[PDB]
Length: 99
Image (cartoon, rainbow, N blue to C red; front, side, top):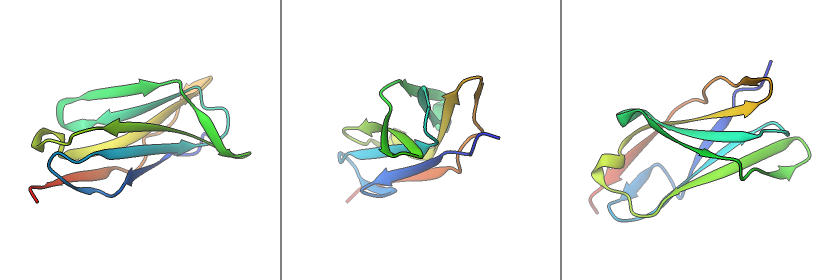
């Protein structure tokens, strides 16, 4: 019923060691919480700092300032739009490029 959210990586999914990456989670209007799921160590980041790009969309961002090899692995977005949590987004595979 709730649309599956989308995940994007900026500047991309292949990232030099020490560089930043920003994950953008997008979903329907009215999302209360976006959660970035970091599969490799089973951790996550939550944010209520949600805003809209348009009337039918909302989004949130998660930045890793300095990527390390430990940041490689699958990432997904999931959102809370009461009453329920959404399905998980398709995964994005973060890969580290030593150079």
